Image 1 (cartoon, rainbow over the protein chains, first blue to last red):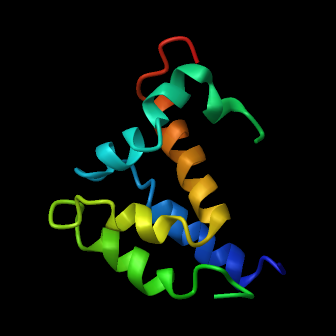
Image 2: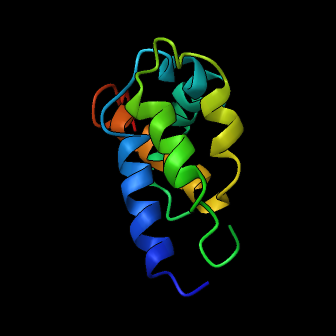
Length: 47
Length: 59
């Protein structure tokens, strides 16, 4: 796209959605295997 | 939701977590999450990043 308003609204939205945590976000994370993706090192990958 | 892919979720995924994940505990996050694929990947990335910054084990 032209990542301008798309960038700025993506940035604030991923900031909300990862602001530390949220009490049902634990399920949303395990529903996406994220606590396993941690030990896989996915946080450290450029993709 | 075409130029920017999330400009609707800018209201609804935003209010889906601005209204806390207690009454918002369900997959209603996950159902709006999927709409902007870069937001979904940025969520998964920064979710994983927040975790390795808390509980890395070996990563």
